[PDB]
Image (cartoon, coloured by chain):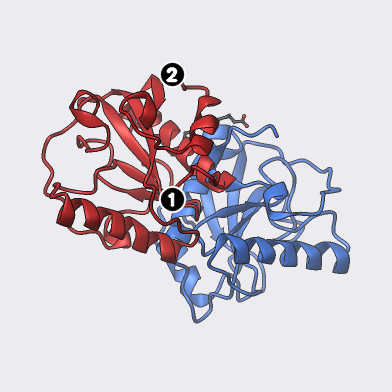
Chain colours: A blue, B red
Amino acid sequence: EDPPACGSIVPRREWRALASECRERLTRPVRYVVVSHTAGSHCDTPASCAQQAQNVQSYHVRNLGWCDVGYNFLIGEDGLVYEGRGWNIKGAHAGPTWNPISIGISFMGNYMNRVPPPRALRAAQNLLACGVALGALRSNYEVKGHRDVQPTLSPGDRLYEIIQTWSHYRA
Amino acid sequence: EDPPACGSIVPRREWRALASECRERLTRPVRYVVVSHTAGSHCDTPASCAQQAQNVQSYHVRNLGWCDVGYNFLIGEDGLVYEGRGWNIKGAHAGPTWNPISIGISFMGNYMNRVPPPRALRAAQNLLACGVALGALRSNYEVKGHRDVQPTLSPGDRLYEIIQTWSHYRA
Ligand SMILES: CCCCCCCCCCCCCCCC(=O)O
């Protein structure tokens, strides 16, 4: 229901997601974007990646007791973006400092010794673009690695060096 | 014009397409979008869909002797948009009356007794928005079924019924 909709995103319902219980909202236009990797399994198909979105969310909700999967968005290697908390709800990916002043997107998989296909990178940037068009993101926006803000290897050596060559990337 | 690049499209190089020998351009902004199906085998993974787009292009160039894949864009059930002749080049999808004044989008598969998945419909729709934003399509552009402009079943009863419900569909 109620879809138009931008950057070709797989809606929560499409991926058979449990419902959110999160309330805290993000004050848009948002300034930062933090890229992480789930550090979980990778997947390269609509089917496999939906099952992985579930797996990630399930771990976050049933096990860490969170109100919803931690990320605002998840990127699959199938080149599709999966809906997490979204543009409006504050995420849980970067620590109390960074969670309310940024959107966090996560690439499903471990990218330490592996690199994400061009399509996933496309879906990523394309995702950010839609964000500006929406007022959710800030056109002047800045990109940061998960590791650029938290003692963590995330989003992986391989992927980390790519987002640095991104134009909107700041260190 | 309107600089920022739009949406996620799998480029030619990526699905391994033969080089295009087409030269006749379209006059921007285009007023019509004609939707068809390939009535060929469907595909639901980036991997399998790239092959299929190739099979379709192949069949058009090698067997029908066209300058390129007939469609301007192809949609896969993997939820991805496959680049063909693209926005600026007259295609070969709908006859001499319609090929000079329209964009042809084809859904890979036969949608007579199957509907395409939401991710497919979503990609197709997001693409059209991309066209508008770019100025390749009129903001008031009109979507037509292939059967509405030529005598064919394509784009399939199921998919035809769906596009009828689109904001820009005019029989
Ligand atoms: C290049 C970046 C993406 C731009 C693509 C065009 C954006 C138009 C599509 C916006 C979605 C239409 C509905 C409005 C949003 C909503 O209802 O939530």
- Give x and y (percent) for residue A24: 82, 43
Residue B34: give its label: none
- Give x and y (percent) for residue A43: 57, 69
Task: Label 2, secondary structure: give it.
Answer: loop
Earlier along the polypeptide chain: callout 1 or callout 2?
Answer: 1
Asked if residue A113 is positioned above or below residue A162 in the image, the reply reads: below
Residue B171: give its label: 2
Asked if residue A78 is positioned above or below residue A8 in the image, the reply reads: below
Q: Chain of mark 1?
A: B
- Residue at left offset 69%, top offset 56%: A71
Task: Give the quarter of the image for residue B128.
Answer: top left
The alpha-carbon separation of the residues under discs 1 and 2 comes to 23 Å
- Give x and y (percent) for residue A34: 60, 57
Please state which of residues A66 and B112 is positioned toward the viewer in this rendering. B112
- Residue at left offset 53%, top offset 37%: B158
Asked if the beta carbon under badge 1 is closer than 8 A to the nearest atom of ligand 1, the reply is: no
Q: Quadrant of the N terminus of chain A?
A: top right
User: Which amino acid type corresponds to the residue marked 2 in the rendered image?
Assistant: Ala
- Residue at left offset 38%, top offset 29%: B147
Instruction: Give the residue number, with chain letter if any, for mark 1.
Output: B109
Q: How many marks?
A: 2
Residue A144 in sight: yes
Tell me if mark 2 has few (under 14), some (14-19) or many (20+) residues whose alpha carbon lies within 10 angstroms of its own. Answer: few
Residue A139 in sight: no
Task: Label 1, secondary structure: give it.
Answer: loop
Q: Chain of mark 2?
A: B
User: Which amino acid type corresponds to the residue marked 1 in the rendered image?
Assistant: Gly
